[PDB]
Image (cartoon, rainbow over all chains, first blue to last red; front, side, top):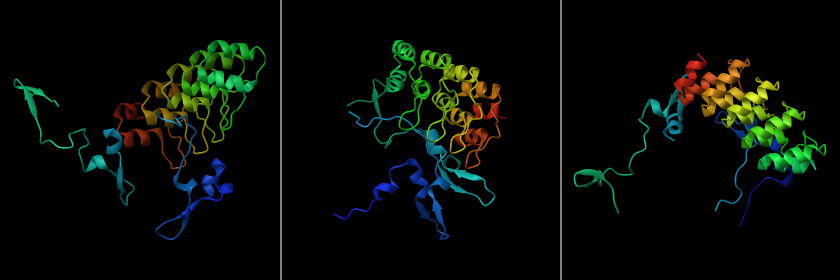
Length: 48
Length: 48
Length: 153
C-alpha cells in the first residue's frame, strides 16, 4: 500500500488544526481556523 | 431530523441572503416508496 | 488525589466528592483537555456535586484548552438548575470560547428556551457575535425556531 498522512508532530495538539491550509477556487490558501470551530465532548470509543 | 435537512444551505445570494433547502422543498419523514398500502377490515394497517 | 475527584465528579458519586474534598483535593484539578470537576459535573448533569464544588470554592470561570466554561456545557446540554446555580455563583454569562461562542449561542442552538431566558436575565449580550459574526437570533432564524426568535426580538 501507499499511505499519505501528517508527520506525527503536526497531528498531536488541538492547536495543530490551524496549521493545515486548503486552497480555495480563487487560489488563496485558507487555514482550518478560518472556516471551522471546535469544542471538547464525550463519546463511545466502542459501540456494541 | 427534517429540521436539520431544512436548514441545509444551497447557496448565499449576492446581497448576503441565504437559500436553504426548505426554501425550494418540503422536508418530511415519508416512505422509500408509496407503492404498497395495506388495510385490515378496511382500517389502515401494515404487516409482514 | 485530584484525579479521584475528576472521576468522582464525572460518575456523579455525591458521597465520594465530599470525602475527597475533606482531604483538600485540588477542586480546580484539570484533566488532559483542561476539564475541572465542575466541567464534568456541568456536562453529565450532576446538580448536587456542582453546588458542593462551588461551596468548596471551585473556579466558576475555569476554562478548558479551547476556552469552554462549565456554563457553556450546562447551557448547551439543557441543564436549567445547573445554569442558575453557576450564574448565582457569579459565572461570566458573556464568557467566550476560542471560537467566540457564548453560553447563549449554545443554549439557543439546541433550543433550550427556559435556559435562554435565565441567561438574558443575567445580562447575556444578545448582539454578541462568534468568529463567523452570528448572533443567537441568526441561529434561531437559521434553525427556524420561531418561539426562540420571539424572545430575542
